Image (tube, coloured by chain):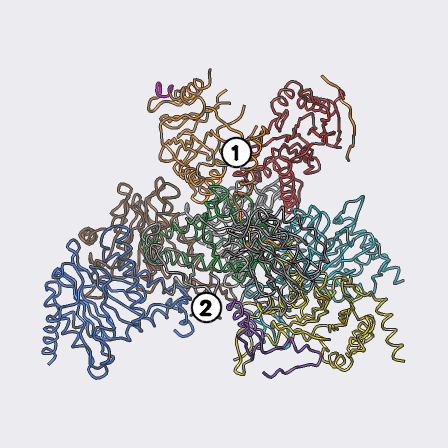
Amino acid sequence: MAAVSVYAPPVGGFSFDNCRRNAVLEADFAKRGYKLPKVRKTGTTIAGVVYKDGIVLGADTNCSKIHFISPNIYCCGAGTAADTDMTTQLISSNLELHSLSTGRLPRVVTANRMLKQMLFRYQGYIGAALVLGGVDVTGPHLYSIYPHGSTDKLPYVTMGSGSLAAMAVFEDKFRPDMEEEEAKNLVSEAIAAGIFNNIDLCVISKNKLDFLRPYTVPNKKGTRLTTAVLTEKITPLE
Amino acid sequence: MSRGSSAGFDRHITIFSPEGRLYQVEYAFKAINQGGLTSVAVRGKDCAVIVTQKKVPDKLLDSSTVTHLFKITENIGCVMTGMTADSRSQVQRARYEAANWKYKYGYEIPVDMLCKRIADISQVYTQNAEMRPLGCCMILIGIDEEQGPQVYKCDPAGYYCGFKATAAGVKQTESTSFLEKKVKKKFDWTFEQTVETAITCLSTVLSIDFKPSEIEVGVVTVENPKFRILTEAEIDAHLVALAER
Amino acid sequence: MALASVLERPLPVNQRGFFGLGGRADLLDLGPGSLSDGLSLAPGIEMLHGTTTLAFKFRHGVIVAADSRTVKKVIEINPYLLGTMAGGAADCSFWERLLARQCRIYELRNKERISVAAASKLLANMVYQYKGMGLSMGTMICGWDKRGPGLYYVDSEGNRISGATFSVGSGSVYAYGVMDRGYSYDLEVEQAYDLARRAIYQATYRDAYSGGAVNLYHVREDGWIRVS
Amino acid sequence: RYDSRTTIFSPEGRLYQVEYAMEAIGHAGTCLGILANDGVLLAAERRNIHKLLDEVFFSEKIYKLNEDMACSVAGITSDANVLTNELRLIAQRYLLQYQEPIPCEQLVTALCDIKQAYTQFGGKRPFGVSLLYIGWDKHYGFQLYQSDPSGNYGGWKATCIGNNSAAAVSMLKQDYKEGEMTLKSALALAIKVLNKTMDVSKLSAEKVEIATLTRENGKTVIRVLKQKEVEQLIKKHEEEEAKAER
Amino acid sequence: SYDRAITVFSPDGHLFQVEYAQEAVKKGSTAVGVRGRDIVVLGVEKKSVAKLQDERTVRKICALDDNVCMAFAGLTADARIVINRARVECQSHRLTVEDPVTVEYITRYIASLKQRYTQSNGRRPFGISALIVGFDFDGTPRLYQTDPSGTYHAWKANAIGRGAKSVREFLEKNYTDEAIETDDLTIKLVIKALLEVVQSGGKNIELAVMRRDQSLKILNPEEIEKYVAEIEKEKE
Amino acid sequence: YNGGAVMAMKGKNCVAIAADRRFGIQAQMVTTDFQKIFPMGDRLYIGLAGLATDVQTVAQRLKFRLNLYELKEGRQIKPYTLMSMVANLLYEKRFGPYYTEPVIAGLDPKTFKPFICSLDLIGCPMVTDDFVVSGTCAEQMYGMCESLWEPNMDPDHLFETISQAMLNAVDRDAVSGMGVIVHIIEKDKITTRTLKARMD
Amino acid sequence: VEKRITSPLMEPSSIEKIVEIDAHIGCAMSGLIADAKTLIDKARVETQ
Amino acid sequence: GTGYDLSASTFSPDGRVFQVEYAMKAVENSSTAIGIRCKDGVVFGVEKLVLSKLYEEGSNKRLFNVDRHVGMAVAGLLADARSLADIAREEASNFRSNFGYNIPLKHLADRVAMYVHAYTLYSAVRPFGCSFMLGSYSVNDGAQLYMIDPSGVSYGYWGCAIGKARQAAKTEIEKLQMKEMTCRDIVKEVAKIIYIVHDEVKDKAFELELSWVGELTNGRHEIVPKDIREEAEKYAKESLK
Amino acid sequence: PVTELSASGPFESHDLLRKGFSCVKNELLPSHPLELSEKNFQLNQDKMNFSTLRNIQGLFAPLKLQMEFKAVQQVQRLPFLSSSNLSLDVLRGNDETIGFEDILNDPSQSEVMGEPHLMVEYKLGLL
Amino acid sequence: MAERGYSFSLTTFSPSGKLVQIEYALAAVAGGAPSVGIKAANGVVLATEKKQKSILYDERSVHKVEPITKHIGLVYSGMGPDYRVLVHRARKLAQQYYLVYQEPIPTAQLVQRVASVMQEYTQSGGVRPFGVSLLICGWNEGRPYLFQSDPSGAYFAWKATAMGKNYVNGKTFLEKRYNEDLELEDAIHTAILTLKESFEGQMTEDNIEVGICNEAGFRRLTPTEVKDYLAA
């Protein structure tokens, strides 16, 4: 149409309009009790351990909190729901581009770097606290990235509401080099101790994963899972 | 020089000829021969070896400053063939790009990814009218993680490819024929056999019996992944061991 | 050097004095008393203030009048255009000096004098750009153009009101009253009313600070005059 | 004085590079547009008629821009792709700001400003595309515009662009009746003209694509005729030409 | 020392690229503008009308604001660009100073735009000349003309385009104070000037008048034919 | 200010989307009675509860993007793809969001399988297969929808159930001037009904 | 200055080769008018 | 290489950038500078040509101080040589500011040589028509001598000569066993070599410009003191005959 | 309190119809902490990279990167039409990463674009 | 052959309206290694000839048949570096489409976006067209796609095509042997035969490259699979 008020071409990214408007509007509404919409949070217990030849990642459930980042890397998220979703999707597509160029299946440190530098870029304003974990040619790696851009490479880690009970269970019963069943039971038990007042489980194992064949794109599927009336008007269409 | 494009089918980089050929890129390929030096890189069972001529035509010139083997990362080394300043500038660019990769991705750059990055930059040079190709060839070596030794060759056109053995310079065709004949027979050369192969290729296509001061050898090994440049004593040991046989 | 010049950044790395994420950066910020003087386009808490003013249109012109005297209460924009002061003294003086600069540039370009509507609109734009930043203006632009006598009230809050009777200040309420007027007053009778109105301000005061006579004015067709 | 740049006038005031840009369309396929009392149409010659070419998007040449407009390009195909994308963008920007569909001449004017900008700034090749627009708006009703590489548009009641546009225009000018055109007579005239100007081959309903625009129950209906209808039109023309002979 | 660059003087001191843009102007249809007493008139020849054309779309007389109008001769696409910039500038000036543009203000703006494009040999001048008629805010009729170089002057009557010289000779010999007394005489004088280059007159003539305090009015072919019939009667 | 309440339910090869209407109101301040449900397709609708200005802005920008998508791809958009477009727009605010929270309710134009969804103001979608609610009264709306929703409903039972849930959710013993508009999307037709509580 | 009026139909007041920069300065022009007026406006704005 | 030699971004049909070759000939346009590296330092010497008797002695110097420890001897266009002296000074100061110690001479040579090369790459700038030598001394590094030419190629030398008579001077340097001489004997021999290759008829009335950096200056670049320069000039004259 | 009113000389002229609604009153304190961090992110990343290149390698390295960036950004598309930045991304290293500038608020479908000539001659520094 | 400088500028039309620098970029494509695309009834085949034909090439290194997503794959004939730069761009565009719409990009959409990039490079001046013409094979909506995008940025949907050297004879060969009801296996046989038409000597599994696209997605055949196809 050619707007008269446009001199330079628009760019992409976050918009930052509505910022001052929302500040004034939220101060005004809070002085009247009007309850603007809020963001969805996903605070639930997420936990992970490294066993001898893999990791086990676990979460509470009715939802699915264990994200996909790579055929060898998976992620659990706590914090703002939209933030964990978008964060993991962006890093998953970046790791697809990386692997599709390199022809190698990704590295967990690459995902950790991407996540921590993206979360550092947005100065804690993206509320994604993650439990990253995967398996490369280097071995099983478990990380815990925090919304401000700080990671922590760990043997076991827990986040969410029951994180203290689950961390207590891990400090009680975690041993280096467990079996797949032992580690699976430990992660389930830590989650359960974190919920009581189902449980998802992701198992990435070194001997279920070939790091010598060329990388090929995986196939993906999807997620997200009286009184009487008086009809004043009716209007069928078509 | 100021600005514009030279008119002619072989006089600007962004002009095609009637046959769809970029002639300035081919002239850059001829610039690789400016220097009169040949480089051989040979990949073995568990090592990669780069061998280049070391001509120092000056008694007054400090010979420890003449070198064409460079260290890109701690575990990647390259032999540069072509114009000397262009070679050193492309080494500087490869060093920067490798450091950026380690920064962004948290692990050290592979060899194929480094030659791919350098070749992407070279393609950008061939497509734009302000820049020109570099008259140099980069042959990179490294030990990857699970593939093994790697020899890769970027070139002025932006083309790159992995090899089992490759050559650049004046005697590139003669060396390529020599190495083809060698690789058809057997290829699992241990470590000594790869060094002998590289030195024999260089000393056959040049018909020159070498001295430890007329030749440079840089190696990587699976057990010692770090790029290493052999001292004159080590090259002389290899040469005497080749001569006795 | 030629390469950094062909680049035309200028950015603090392609220069001299760079030793980190910045360093001295060609003078650690130190510079010069300007690179350009004026004659070209290029914490002190005690600013000054004003008091009482009238202004009515007419049949024979526009009549400004201010609470006597010293201090200044009417800015003399140029021979054909007047303006009063309220709020910050520096604000009124500076922005109407800029307005007189605009009016003279207009007259030079267009060979005819600016209209009062255009002049007041230029002033309203200049002070509206910095709305909410603390500018305090209460001017009142009056003149005479091809449309007859003109009278506008231009404010630092974006207001620009046309009218045939205005009044700003303390005695404003008493001075707008006592403004029992008619569009066809004789000139002497007009001077009479403006005198009487600034007086009915000061019938509760007398000559002193912002006190004296009436600093009367009169915008004729060929430019204003000072009646007394 | 010469013809190397778009930003150079010859010493008789001619912009030779723009004239050469406009010379590229005379190679392209014949696009024909006819305005009737109850609709508009676009008849376009399918230039790409090779055996191994796939059955493609609903039309090779006809593009939908709105709910209300369609275009039909002739010239360089890649420039045309860029230009139709920008047409659709311009129209959605008008709809976003005014909440009303863009009027047809405003869209044509905006695209032609883009094309003129490419004929005015140096170091930018003009668009070798001549478009042909058909639409409906509440101001002027059914409209048919034309545009050429110089960003120079005009509204017509019947026009042709592309190969043999001059013979087609002579035939339309001889046979188009102003005021007494209906969409069936416009389709007959389109087949007749598009036949006599495609004399490199015999006309068949595989080398022509026809799209009509009408208004039905308060909505515009841009419809690309099916292959089994263009055959019926061609038969009607052949029987007419047999009768008019003997 | 030649043409082929916009910003290069020839050894005689001529910028030839601007002069060739003015050559581009001298091929366009003739536009005649006459400034009257209380009416200002514009007339353009409709050169080589095609019968299958919507004439509304190829008009060469345009309104810039409610008091200013403009006819052009030259390349029509450049003219469209310049016209729309002038329209935005008329509205922007109203926003700046509340007062309607004087015809000189918008003439000056149009000339400054054309002059911006006569610099910088990476750009191309506008190959148009314009006849900007109008009424000032105090009611004075004006007629200005700009040319591709960025040069404007005020006229009493003028012609631009092909055959501007014959029409301007006719206007000089025939523009008096007795040809201006009424609105009708001004209209007939413009039509008579245009009939000096137009064959088969009346159907190749596009008149538009602007009376004081009134908007631009395009005369339909019926009114134009009535005026032409009056002219032939006055020929006796 | 009342943001409103938008609901959607699934039946058997049919979807329902409902929102309140505010028949009788002479309120003031920010707009209250706005249009909430926008047809985004032949069998696709979006409901937008929240600040009225942001509802209109989101609807208009969504229609911009959707119209462009449908012209470029030459196909009718699918409900899940509309969900993803809405999420992308909502999230491109994110730091200063739109105070709107949508529900998508439509029928897939290949198998006419119901799709319902509900996002938040930054676009985190929740795809359920029974019902969704969106608004400032989500708690009792959820309670009523859980108590009344039955699997494999038909258009009439769907209409009855969604009307009952809306009415008895916004109830507060205050259904006076409270209306409900209900669109029932089916493979063949779309039936819009505007209704009032019988108490009045 | 020599005016060189081209047509009798042209307002002489619009082709003035002597302009006023300020009340005490005046310019006489010769050459390209479009450039001259740029320099004249620079002078006027500079004086103000 | 006509037709392929107007830009520094054009390759000749045999892979030769000819603007860079013409820039190196530009270096051959000027009078000679030699630099000799010895057992305990580096000595520079320039056959500086007296343009006029009106110039204050010391003007048009061609022996710069690039850092406290580095000295630079130039040839070619003198404006280009001064710009490159400014660049080298900037590099040394920037390194010291970042990293807190004196820049190694090899690293300085790389930085400046890579600048010169960057000019040999574009159509927007022309190659530097100037060649220069850097020379330093550190207790932990020994004497070091580098020469950069207009193409951006820097090597390390034991003796270098740049300028008009680089070949004759190079022949004369090769006779010196500089690896086992101190800076004093090298100063005398540098003066001798400057006097030998001077062309007394074509060029006229030159003045020696001697400089050292060594352990006799404690790793600090300096002008050879007036008395030692007088002794060196007298030796050089008496050896010429 | 920003000071800086060039007000010594606040003689600048603006186009009123094209300036839209500008509020210099609030153009001194960004609307969000992340507003400028995101607006100038490629700028700040280039400055960080040029700084590390300068400090490690020398003047030549940022100069050559800036010269390549300037060259590729100049054989482009006129500002009223979207470009791909294919060569610029290959130079900067964004040919294999997707950020949030790439997926959010797509520049290719701007929802608002100015006049062709006005946008071209603004890029040319003519206003 | 310098038509008054109409030959050397990309932004100058010739007096006849030709742009004879984009058709010189089409002579780089017609001087590249042969490529074949055959759209069968249940899949597409992309067969090319490798330039890396000697024993000294690592064949886990660089490939001419590349995947864009799971369902889209490319081959080219022309200039290899231009192909690589366009391949990384096509992969980025596909991932942006996924990130926005949560669905794999359709083949036609990808072809359109890549062609717009190429067109941009044919209009500025100071830049050079791309010396590659791509073949894009994809599988969407239970329907195979074969497209071709040439240096000008103008893409074509094909049933079968041939690029690179000797492509007119290749297309003539393909016309006589392509039928719509062809199955993917017979398509692979026909594509290998069409490559064998214009081929420089004995054809091994190590000097040709094949990639297929069916319901399961795009896949590059291993040298053993190509060896088996060649043996029949």
Camera-side residue of F146 and C159: C159
Residue furthest top as drawn: A197
- Quote the CA–CA distance across marks 1 and 2: 51 Å
Residue C105 lies in magenta, yes or no? no
Q: Which residues are magenta?
A: A168-173
Q: Is residue I97 left or right of residue D211?
A: left
Report the chain shown in green: I
Is residue A192 placed above or below I76 in the rendered structure?
above
The x, y position of residue J13, in whole percent, is 59, 67
Q: Are marks 1 and 2 on the same chain?
A: no
User: With E155 as the anchor, is J155 left or right in this view?
Assistant: left
Q: Which chain is in purple here? A: G
Among the chains pictured, the one given orange colouring is A
- Toward which corner of the image does residue E121 lie, by quadrant? bottom right
Tell me the chief SS of the magenta region: helix
Q: Tell me which amino acid carries mark 1.
A: Ala
The tint of chain B in the picture is brown
Q: Chain F's shade in the image?
A: red
Which chain does the yellow colour mark?
E
Answer with the quarter of the image where residue J43 lies: top right
Which of the chains is cyan? D
Residue A18, visible in the rendered structure: yes
Q: Is residue F54 above or below residue C62?
A: above
Q: Which mark is residue B3?
A: 2
Answer with left or right where residue J154 lies relative to residue E208. left
Give the colour chain H carries in the figure: blue
Point out the frontmost of discs 1 and 2.
1
Secondary structure under badge 1? helix
Residue, disc 1: A82
Chain letter behind tag 2: B
Q: Amino acid at mark 2?
A: Arg
Q: Residue F55 shows which numbered tag?
A: none
